[PDB]
Amino acid sequence: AMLLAPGDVIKRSSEELKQRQIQINLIDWTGRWVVLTEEIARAIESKYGTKIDVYRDEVPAQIIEVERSLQKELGISREGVAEQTERLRDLRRKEKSGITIEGVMSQKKLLSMIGGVERKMAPIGARESAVMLVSNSIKDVVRATAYFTAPTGDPHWKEVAREASKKKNILAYTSTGGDVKTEFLHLIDHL
Amino acid sequence: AMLLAPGDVIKRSSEELKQRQIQINLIDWTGRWVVLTEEIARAIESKYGTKIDVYRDEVPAQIIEVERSLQKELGISREGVAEQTERLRDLRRKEKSGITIEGVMSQKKLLSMIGGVERKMAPIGARESAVMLVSNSIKDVVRATAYFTAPTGDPHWKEVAREASKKKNILAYTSTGGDVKTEFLHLIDHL
Amino acid sequence: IKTTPYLEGDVLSSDSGPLLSVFALQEIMQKVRQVQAD
Amino acid sequence: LLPDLIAGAHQNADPVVLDVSWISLWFAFNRSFEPTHRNEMLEVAPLIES
């Protein structure tokens, strides 16, 4: 299930495409926070799928201080809390021997600050979508099984459309009204 | 079960009529507090049926601070407490960077302050009362099945009484002593 | 009376096209030409 | 024709085969045929036949 689409559409929907795990092949035409210790970052990455960096005495930076509430929420062990507060004491001593720390302690604050949205409660299928690749290259026009069109234009889209319409058995979809991105996402969901 | 009554009686008993869910049709003749977050307001509205507004950085106002005791009493989750105290910290910072907050922590204080009385422990019927409408209009005199009279008077009540007494089969009730409102409420309960 | 639109590469169109009496002869002649292609 | 087709060895008659694609069946099931115009030469068939 391989689809061809205008380049601006994939450019605008790259985030959703990455979130739904379809690989992107496109041709162009012309401060973060860190966790005190690696264990908490690993736990939060496992829970939410969000990559988190680790503080390594680099520069005056902004530190995230996970609080007792989220410590209990994430199921963190006693040793993790102990090492977190040990690193906290080390930071206290370092800044007393003359960096900003935030004690985030609500789940919504952490979500609205950084990271990916939590997981929904449905059965997990083998794959999120039935499509593997959406591309905008003439080099793999024979690779495609269907294509999508929009009133928006690309300098190479006309030739690709001509070379794709020549296929004997290919599914063709066109969008005329509403939002192009919403229609494309609905199609990629139902295809 | 539709009733006709003098306008002053319904004017004086509008609160009870609204509380008992009978719709009012009448013709005339001539600072609040807010909750830190929407979740607590929604919970208290579900528990007591009292509409509560939400603080939105409007003006110097009066804030209700639900305390640990009522937090446990209302069955509030950990995240609700966390977000409440996060908003509290935000308010501390806002007023330190130069609004009144009250830490109500007894159930009776909250009841006597604002809101509706708690619920009684009886089986819940399909409907509170058997009557739907009490009105004071000649436009729906044929709508009524019974009417109530009192020594009190209205400029339109005499004509309505004459037009209602002409009905072949209509129940008539009159109050002579005691309190008019109490008699009317007892009648609307037993009818 | 016009046909429902059909996609021409990337643009919709509704032209009737060649007559059915003309299209048939072309197809038959093309099949025959394929017969004596060798 | 049909017994001849079953036998496989044609005699005194030869059909012609046209070739179509997979999606064509579905698209034909949805598209009808409306006879907008009649044949122009329909009025003069007997003369050319004779």
Image: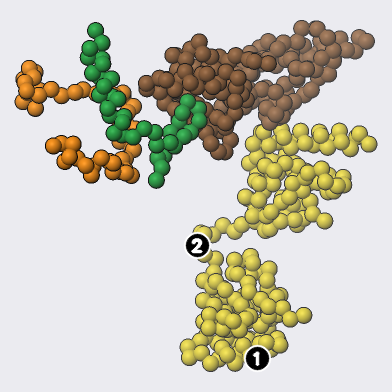
Chain colours: A brown, B yellow, C green, D orange
In the image, what residue occupies the spot 50% across and 27% down? C10
Nearest the camera: A83 or A188? A188
The quarter in which the C terminus of chain A is drawn is top left
Residue A118 image point, x, y percent: 60, 27
Closer to the camera, B92 or B140? B140
Q: Is residue B110 visible?
A: yes
Q: CA distance from mark 2 to mark 1?
A: 37 Å
- Amino acid identity at mark 2: Gly
Q: Position of residue B22 (x, y in %)?
A: 59, 69
Left or right, A144 with respect to A27, comes to left
The chain holding disc 1 is: B
Pointer 1 residue: B158
Could you say which quadrant of the image residue D44 lies in? top left
Q: Which residue is rendered at x = 53% and y = 83% of the image? A: B142
**Residue B125 numbered tag:** 2
Report the chain holding disc 2: B
Of residues B188 and A150, the one nearer the viewer is A150
Q: Dot 2 surroundings within 10 Å: few (below 14), some, or many (20 or more)?
A: few
Residue at image x 39%, y 36%? C16
The reply to whether residue A127 is visible in this rendering is no
Q: Which quadrant of the rendered structure holds the N terminus of chain A?
A: top left
Q: Dot 1 lies on which element?
A: helix
Along the line of sight, which residue is nearer the eye, A80 or B127?
B127
Does B147 appear above or below B98?
below
- Residue A176 vs B35, above or below: the answer is above
